[PDB]
Amino acid sequence: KSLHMYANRLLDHRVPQTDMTFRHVGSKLIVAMSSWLQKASGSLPYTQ
Amino acid sequence: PVYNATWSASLKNKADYVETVLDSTCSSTVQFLEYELNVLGTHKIEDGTLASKTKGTFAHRDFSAEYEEDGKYEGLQEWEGKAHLNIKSPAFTDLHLRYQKDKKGISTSAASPAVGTVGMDMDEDDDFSKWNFYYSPQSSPDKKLTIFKTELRVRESDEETQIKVNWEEEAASGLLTSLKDNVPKATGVLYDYVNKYHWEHTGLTLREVSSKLRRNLQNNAEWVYQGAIRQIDDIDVRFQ
Amino acid sequence: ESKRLIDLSIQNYHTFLIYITELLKKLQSTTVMNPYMKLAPGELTIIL
């Protein structure tokens, strides 16, 4: 519940004159991390 | 002969009440530097309580200031009365300030022809209290835009107490627009003011004086330049 | 330039207050402790 409400807080606020929430930037960084992970050798189901 | 100024003051005791009279005036060869200021205040201490009535009025070319005070002073924390200020400025905008204080309510506001009317009212009572800070638009003196409001309410049932704070974005935005629109209003009055004084003394505008300064700079530059050129021929000829 | 500054100030002030109200509402949803806070657009009420 605490993580849910924190995510709601993060989603619901951003600086004026920009409507892109920081969660999209977080998702972009997560995508980059996942791309690097799949690039990394020694893959395991735990990585999946 | 050029300048004459008189400062007259007098403190007088008349049995039950004191009277304060102040006068000040100046006669000058400068037109906008002559005035007369006057104030009168009667002060009666009745069995320890003070009843106060005073009038202060100013006269000058660019405006006149007129203030009225009335009321009484009980102890050091109970003043009940009214204070009214009215300013008539040909040089700039006029103003009229009204202050009121009763034992259960304080009300005061300022009526400005540029900003409008800005006022605040404090109603105080044992079990409730309310602060109101409102801005009436210059274009609409019939309504009050609540800049902010506070409402203290101690519940007579149970031990709960409510604090209610309210504000209007509309009031703030309207006041900000009025202020940004007021910039040229002050700019023009001050510009015409300085030009008026320049006229009263030398008959020139600020821009006219700037042009005169530029022209004199050019004239002096040529005065230097001609001699600078001539010296070359002088030196050459003497060397020959 | 003065008028432009005041215009931008009003613009960002308005664009910003709504995000603040949303964040405040999400935060108030977090807890229900005995002192009860009620948030409204342009208003806040405090019960003690």
Image (cartoon, rainbow, N blue to C red):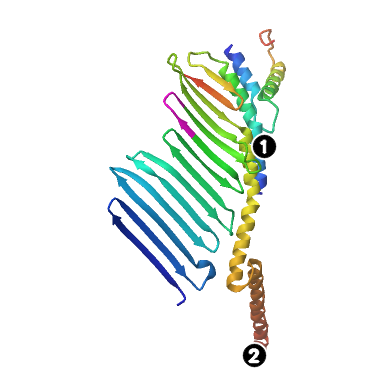
Quadrant housing residue B199: bottom right
Asked if residue B17 is positioned above or below residue B109 in the image, the reply reads below
Query: Is residue B123 rendered magenta in the image?
Result: yes
Q: Which residue is drawn at 61% across and 48% down?
A: B114
Asked if residue B240 is positioned above or below residue B67 in the image, the reply reads below
Residue B11, position as x, y percentages in the image? 32, 58
Q: Which residue is drawn at 32% across and 53% down?
A: B18
How many numbered markers are drawn? 2
The N terminus of chain B is located in which quarter?
A: bottom left
Range covered by the magenta-colored residues: B122-128
* Closer to the camera in the image, B225 or B105: B105
Query: Is residue B85 rendered magenta in the image?
Result: no
The C terminus of chain B is located in which quarter?
A: bottom right
Residue A21, position as x, y percentages in the image? 68, 25
Residue B43, position as x, y percentages in the image? 34, 50
* Closer to the camera in the image, C41 or B27: B27
What is the chain letter for disc 1?
C
Q: Where does label 1 land, which residue?
A: C11
Give the number of the disc on residue B239.
2
Residue B222, position as x, y percentages in the image? 67, 79
